[PDB]
Amino acid sequence: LSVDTKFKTEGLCVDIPGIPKDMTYRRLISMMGFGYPNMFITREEAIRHVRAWIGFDVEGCPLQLGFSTGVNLVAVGLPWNVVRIKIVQMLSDTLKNLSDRVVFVLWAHGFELTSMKYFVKIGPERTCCLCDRRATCFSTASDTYACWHHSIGFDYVYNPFMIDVQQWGFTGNLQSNHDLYCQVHGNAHVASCDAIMTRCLAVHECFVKRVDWTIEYPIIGDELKINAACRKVQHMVVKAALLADKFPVLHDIGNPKAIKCVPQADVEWKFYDAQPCSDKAYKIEELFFTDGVCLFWNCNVDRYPANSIVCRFDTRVLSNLNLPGCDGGSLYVNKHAFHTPAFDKSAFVNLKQLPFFYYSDSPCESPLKSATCITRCNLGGAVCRHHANEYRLYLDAYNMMISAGFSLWVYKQFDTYNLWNTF
Ligand SMILES: O=C(NCc1nc(C2CC2)cs1)c1cc(CNCC2CC2)[nH]n1
Ligand SMILES: [Zn+2]
Ligand SMILES: [Zn+2]
Ligand SMILES: [Zn+2]
Image 1 (cartoon, rainbow, N blue to C red):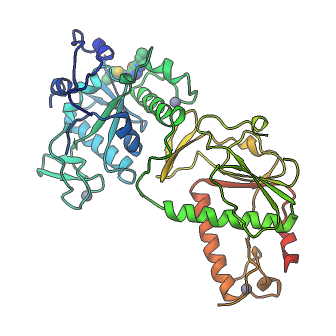
Image 2 (cartoon, rainbow, N blue to C red):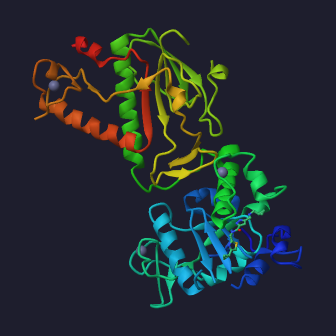
Image 3 (cartoon, rainbow, N blue to C red):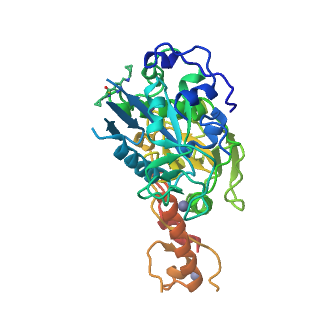
């Protein structure tokens, strides 16, 4: 983002009367008092760094500093020299396991930008004094720099980034634009409410209305183990449903790039294309199947049919992979960014929770007691060691997937008792 790019200033002219209409980022940054070519960034760079987004609003009358973490600080009610210490602590704790930077998302009216100099220092890109991550904070006590992990006691935010949502060409104020898409965040006339709304609207614009599944996001947690667990569980559960109930046809509704998850199964496999719905859940009436079984693997519909196998992401889950989203939805970032419509328990009324089970027909070849280890093994009274090992690996994956937020549902007649006679 060129510092010579033009910045529209109408939003700022109520806090800053007489501000020039003709303004560049270069001159704004100067007016604000200030590897790092611009404090501001493009919508594209911002999207690549969605994990760093912290909505931010400042409201005057002595100022109130609201952030999308729900926090409201008053700077005078306490002086700035303590308020900046709290800001560093809050952002470091919020972001250390998410991103290597902060990106302040704004609906800029002026106070938020003029307040920055009181808690931000800028300069050349640097590295942490105690590790190799880029520096995000600075301390004036020790003249040293630190990342989010090592910033305890540090008092200034260092080389923050920011983006003003009002530059994207909106009509009317923040609430009137946010409420067009979202009924979950209110307008309680505290600064944090605006900050939360600002981020929500930004997420809606970049991930609900606009979608880019080509953007990749760095590994920050159990991504790989989780995705592997999901493939393992998917194969297990679908294979067992075909054996227990012997459906003649399976209707695989969802990703157009889907491959048969149980390739050796007898059934007639029919695919139906539906991209991840990022806004509202698909209506099963538009999508549509009563023959056999329907596989909705992360295909969010509003009411699943009774003859389904379903894996559905639970947006309420607290994890580093799952960011708060728009209108109760969540932004699940695991390699790619998937805004997900809000979890709705009623979608599953025709189904039941799927119980844990492990099923294997593999030879017993290389002490576990479990009623859910479904193997010739246990049928004959004593689980062999190989199936004990596999059982404990599968449980681990299964638990990994559930705790990552996924939930599993199945048709009501599913009964693992029917699998024992496949031995
Ligand atoms: O009164 C708001 N904060 C509370 C505040 N305490 C202070 C003093 C330090 C104690 C200053 S301000 C507030 C007002 C809004 C309005 N946002 C939407 C605009 C109206 C279209 N947001 N927060
Ligand atoms: Zn560090
Ligand atoms: Zn919202
Ligand atoms: Zn065995």
